[PDB]
Amino acid sequence: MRECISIHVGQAGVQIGNACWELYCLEHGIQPDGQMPSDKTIGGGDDSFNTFFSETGAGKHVPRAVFVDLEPTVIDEVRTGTYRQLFHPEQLITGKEDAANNYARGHYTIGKEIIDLVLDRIRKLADQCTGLQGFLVFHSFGGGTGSGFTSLLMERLSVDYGKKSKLEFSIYPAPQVSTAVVEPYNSILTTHTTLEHSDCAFMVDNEAIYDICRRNLDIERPTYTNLNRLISQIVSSITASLRFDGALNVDLTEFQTNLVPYPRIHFPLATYAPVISAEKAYHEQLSVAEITNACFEPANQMVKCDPRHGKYMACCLLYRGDVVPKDVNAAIATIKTKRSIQFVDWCPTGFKVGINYQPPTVVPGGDLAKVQRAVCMLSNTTAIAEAWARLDHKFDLMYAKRAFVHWYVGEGMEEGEFSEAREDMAALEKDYEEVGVD
Amino acid sequence: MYTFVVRDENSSVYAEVSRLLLATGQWKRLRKDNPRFNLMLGERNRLPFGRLGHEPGLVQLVNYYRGADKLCRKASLVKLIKTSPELSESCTWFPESYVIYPTTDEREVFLAAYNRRREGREGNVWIAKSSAGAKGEGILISSEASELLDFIDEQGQVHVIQKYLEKPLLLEPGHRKFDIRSWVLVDHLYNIYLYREGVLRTSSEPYNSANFQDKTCHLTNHCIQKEYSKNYGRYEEGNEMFFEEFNQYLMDALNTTLENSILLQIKHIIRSCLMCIEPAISTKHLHYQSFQLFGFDFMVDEELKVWLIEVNGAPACAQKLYAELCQGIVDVAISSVFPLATSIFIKLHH
Amino acid sequence: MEVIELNKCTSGQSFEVILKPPSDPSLEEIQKKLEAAEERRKYQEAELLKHLAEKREHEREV
Amino acid sequence: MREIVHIQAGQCGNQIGAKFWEVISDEHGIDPTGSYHGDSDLQLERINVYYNEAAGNKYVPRAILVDLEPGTMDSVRSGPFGQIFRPDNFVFGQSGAGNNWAKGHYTEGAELVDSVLDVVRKESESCDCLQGFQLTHSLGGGTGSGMGTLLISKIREEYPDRIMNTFSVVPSPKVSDTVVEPYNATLSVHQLVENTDETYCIDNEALYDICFRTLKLTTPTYGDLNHLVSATMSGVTTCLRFPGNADLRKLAVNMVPFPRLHFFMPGFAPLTSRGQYRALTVPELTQQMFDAKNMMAACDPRHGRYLTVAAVFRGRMSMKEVDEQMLNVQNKNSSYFVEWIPNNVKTAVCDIPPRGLKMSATFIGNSTAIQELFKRISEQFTAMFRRKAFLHWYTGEGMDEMEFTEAESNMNDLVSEYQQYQDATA
Ligand SMILES: Nc1nc2c(ncn2[C@@H]2O[C@H](COP(=O)(O)OP(=O)(O)OP(=O)(O)O)[C@@H](O)[C@H]2O)c(=O)[nH]1
Ligand SMILES: Nc1ncnc2c1ncn2[C@@H]1O[C@H](COP(=O)(O)OP(=O)(O)CP(=O)(O)O)[C@@H](O)[C@H]1O
Ligand SMILES: COc1cc(OC)c(-c2coc3c4c(ccc3c2=O)OC(C)(C)C=C4)cc1OC
Ligand SMILES: Nc1nc2c(ncn2[C@@H]2O[C@H](COP(=O)(O)OP(=O)(O)O)[C@@H](O)[C@H]2O)c(=O)[nH]1
Ligand SMILES: [Ca+2]
Ligand SMILES: [Ca+2]
Ligand SMILES: [Ca+2]
Ligand SMILES: [Ca+2]
Ligand SMILES: [Mg+2]
Ligand SMILES: [Mg+2]
Ligand SMILES: [Mg+2]
């Protein structure tokens, strides 16, 4: 058994982290108390769930989690909430005034003052680890903390834990649930600085989640709560192999090995099905073939884009529930004869498959119905570069006028970083295109 | 009211569509780079498909199908026909063709057939073309192979060599050659609409199988006849015979109709090509929707068999039909999505 | 369609299906970036305060 | 806790300041003795942004009251909520400023400014995390204009990393006390260009036209103008005073793309006279809010382009309908939004309405059309300055013509900087 430490940075990172740890506890049968009746090795263990939970002599199961925000109101809700007993004060870290949606302020000004402390509270958890694997880092692209502080943290984690893998769950900005204007700046700034420091990153576009909630949960005006519970489901299906018995994606290194042949192109597309309203009176449960086929509809992707007009480098299918290999392969055969699935020439055309028999757990009173079988597809397709193109175009439009740039310069940054970061992104878009197009 | 943007300066068709929409009083035009458009009349090259469908609360529509180039570029049309089971290695209505690179190449299979033709004492003239050959340039009709294989390598574009249809149908009076241009509109539901009005693009010169290197005898594009040929305009305006004349002619001269003789298999070919690529380009479940106007070019051999020769992704119209057809695009392609306050199209059902 | 590396356990199983074969910055360096930007703030702040001091001197002269 | 320190200076500053404290006190359930008597705890979660807590379940405004004359501050202490205010936060001279910027900024106000800063310090020290300052004042008198902008310069010197925003009342000949207002306003505007992060431009000319033409008040009083001001002030501060995660700096970052262009056009719907049975519809709130008639800066938005826009809807309503109508109004006005700031129109909904209305909306527009306001002031300034008319009131306090010439030039640079971005394209 090798341990994983989860780091949640900024508003989006913290609130998604709470939704995830909530769901983890329900999946492993851990109570808000922190007690796990079914763990019969009291006060210890090297079971698979111990990858994410440590144990106290009193039988309390404690997330291997650090929450970090530069203002305190979000983490205070953690300290008062339903899982307040789960965590310990030194895991929750709050500054006093935030980054004001300003990358430079989260990275340079405020970040310099809290980075050393954060790495100390992280060291305290890494010291409880026999075999630390690495880090899962949750954050927004758009916030000044999520963008600016995260890139600083990621740089220093490469210094202090240089052999360790680092995975990101990153919220890509959507105007429909954002009141900010400068998020394209923060997104390109944090991606440039974090790229050589992240082994594998799962982007989630709030636009896609927001639409899924509206179309399939019949929620006319989704909140962050609605979005985060759906995101937590997807995150759980991605991390389930680190927390349960299995032979696929059992350590963080296997994520890069299976999903990322090129280090720079390390942004796998997630697609999830089925999303079913819990208010549906009557619902006909979907088969292995139907949920698998849904993994190739852009309407179910975490990022809207068209994989037909790109090429695959890798594709994993992660099933939870009543699934056996025969039905998966019958579905894949049928799907291949009717969908445009082009792999790059130098990669094998095929799917790695993991099945876990427990069906997805849903939060009681949430919006998602229980289902008998669900799947999350992780495909490294060049089509996700469409999200880079969108965001770089917004960046270009504003930066040609230097709109808002004075806010960043005012906090110690130089215009040169803007153009340096945007050139990296220009190279990235080219990297994707010579991989995916002829 | 509805908004739209215009990004192909040089499009006869959507120029007139611009005018039509404004004159309805319910369409406002924006500038090239304003993104809160309902409709994009896009550029031909590197249209930013990735940026469409991400404007909150705007239903967005573009006049091109991403991926439709597989059909509308000569090298890739060859590859699509030979590799798609729907069409297959010996599809009956496309000339035996070969993609050949200068300097997945077929230079050897090209010769295997060419050789068996040599010994067969049967017709073995070929033609070699490119998508970069504008206004009649870059093509070579030759009865001896390596005369065209050297013409291929003397420039850097990828070419196709196809068996030249030696025995074409010839109009009378004139002993003159032609090809048929059909305009096809595919809407956001992927309904396939064939404009009822086609046009024949004629040769003013009589055909002459003897000398291939003389070309306005063999090459029917509107421009080359307009510029290179001495007899340009005798029988019909602009070397453009329309369907009513061509039909009345096929009855008088051949005791048959355009419908039975040619159009049945034109409609078959159009459906075969477009249904084949539908899974790859359909926008039915996508966050933006597409339509596109295509120009299909056909040849008719003397047995009244129809051959497909190219598909044009950005076609122009005949002056006579712009009003009618452009108004048809509005009604079928645009107002279908953005409704306002008989028909000229033949729906090819599938 | 070839299946391979099928592993099984009570919690589930996994396998691979193949349809076709194929055809570092230093701690010191960070600390320097963070400190050069802090210096740029201090210099901008000092110019503002010099500007305000000039304004105070004008107020005295009025 | 992100506290705001409020300063009100001069006659206009204190009159509109007191209405503001009256209006939001009622919204938070605080009565004229500072005792809470509300019915929801939404009222108290952000109470501390503007109020200090004193033992005895009292809430005391974090407000400092300044004037060079005692008159208008005796009337504050008289007025409905006069007892609420902390008595040591009344800071007053006796001389008065005579509608003379030079007296407020350089001679009479210089005498009093240190006393004001002692009270500011003693309010800031008691702040867990000071968010910034807001000042209410006019630009046409001497105290709010001249001494108000002196305070802002001093506050910046002592708190240079703190947000300084203002509600600034612009002079108009339609509502006019003296001929020298264009001088006082032009001198003040240059100060504001340099030393505020956000200035809400409350144009007395717009408030007059609104009262006279839409509300059909034939003889508008200061009371009628301030009814509109108070509605707007309650509006813009709604999302600082009730739950919804942006401090003043975060609002400034997303509203101000160039540092000097931070002068906002306010607006409000529905426009009302003092003394509304029909609730408006979300479509009606939206279109009124974007129509020139509801603009409290006498500028035509169709004569410029919006760099950023914010709108705050209040009342129980459909966020779905708000999103739809907002995205609507942007398409019939699509040309009037710059295309090189993507998604520059942002919205909030708060389900607590203002007193006396179940639906209302407040408008915050950063439009390049605001230049019409500064051109108007600059033309009135120049009309007198080309003959050096009335300058002796200012040279008599130590000022030099050159300082007026610089103020004029600085003002016209601001107008040209706006015109630059109104013609900028993508
Ligand atoms: N999915 C999801 N997105 C969120 C959530 N909270 C904020 N966001 C998004 O994050 C972006 C704003 O960045 P934040 O994370 O809120 O800001 P921050 O990380 O706290 O950094 P600061 O600027 O200092 O506040 C917007 O684009 C929001 O849509 C959340 O709970 N769930
Ligand atoms: N296999 C064949 N047999 C006989 N003639 C042929 C032929 N292939 C092409 N041609 C002739 O050559 C001409 C040009 O071919 P093609 O249609 O590819 O050019 P093009 O792509 O410039 C037409 P457009 O301008 O409408 O796109 C045709 O009009 C036709 O008469
Ligand atoms: C000095 O006076 C002030 C004037 C102000 O606006 C005229 C504001 C001010 C309030 O709310 C905002 C909102 C906004 C963006 C900007 C503002 C803003 O800027 O976007 C959404 C997200 C829609 C919410 C409201 C604050 C002030 O500080 C006290
Ligand atoms: N809206 C409004 N404007 C005012 C009021 N009082 C004065 N003004 C305007 O502000 C200018 C002078 O400012 P005033 O407050 O009277 O003098 P100060 O005490 O030096 O600020 C004049 O041009 C007036 O039109 C007020 O109560 N409301
Ligand atoms: Ca155990
Ligand atoms: Ca590394
Ligand atoms: Ca004195
Ligand atoms: Ca002192
Ligand atoms: Mg935050
Ligand atoms: Mg062509
Ligand atoms: Mg007065």
Image (tube, coloured by chain):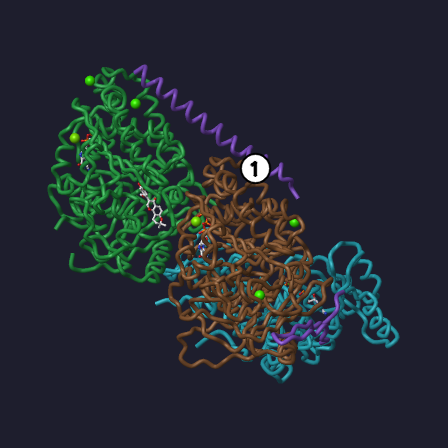
Chain colours: A brown, B cyan, C purple, D green
Q: Is residue B303 above or below residue A18?
A: below
Query: In the image shown, does A165 or A43 lie closer to the viewer?
Result: A43
- Note whether residue B288 is visible: no
Mark 1 Cα-neighbour bin, 10 Å: few <14, some 14–19, many ≥20: few
Q: Is residue B221 above or below residue D91?
A: below
Q: Is residue A319 above or below residue D133?
A: below
Q: Chain letter of disc 1?
A: A
- Note whether residue D78 is visible: yes
Left or right side of D57 for A27: right
Residue at horizontal 81 percent and vertical 71 percent from the top:
B124
In the rendered image, residue D136, in percent from the top left (x then y), is placed at 25, 36
In the rendered image, residue D341, in percent from the top left (x then y), is placed at 44, 46
Q: Quadrant of residue B335?
A: bottom left
Q: Quadrant of the N terminus of chain D?
A: top left
Q: Is residue A150 above or below residue B138?
A: above
Query: In the image shown, does B160 or A207 lie closer to the viewer?
Result: A207
In the rendered image, residue A182, in percent from the top left (x then y), is placed at 46, 46
Secondary element at image label 1:
helix
Report whether the residue tagged 1 is closer than 8 Å to ligand 1: no
Query: In the image shown, does B126 or A353 lie closer to the viewer?
Result: A353
Left or right side of B139 for D393: left
Query: In the image shown, does D256 or D369 lie closer to the viewer?
Result: D256
For badge 1, the amino acid type reads: Gly
Q: Quadrant of residue B157?
A: bottom right
Q: Which residue is mark 1?
A: A416
In the rendered image, residue A346, in percent from the top left (x then y), is placed at 73, 62
